[PDB]
Length: 50
Length: 50
Image (tube, rainbow over all chains, first blue to last red; front, side):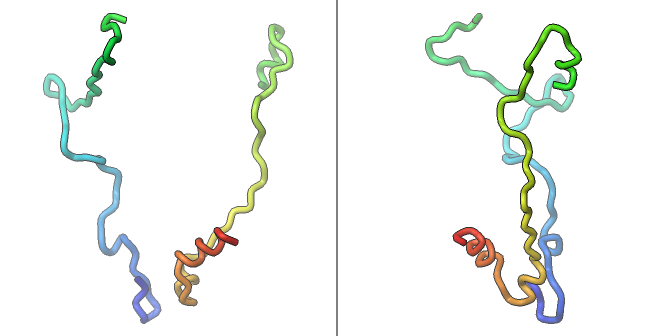
């Protein structure tokens, strides 16, 4: 929005911007240290070892 | 490529797919646009269909 008095307001003046989680819900760590993981589920009919 | 030529073992090492061309980059001014009173919605939607 640009207020009539030769001025403008940008998203900086209303919010804070930055890269963050797409979903802050589920989190994890490993032996204490901060960590992440992808748990893989096997496809019906496939061979575990393979 | 400029190392496959400096190589004995290979010959006729071309790239598949075309290379970079000059592109005409538009650059509409989010400020002057609203100054005049033109919305960005209309400016894009118009450069589109046109």
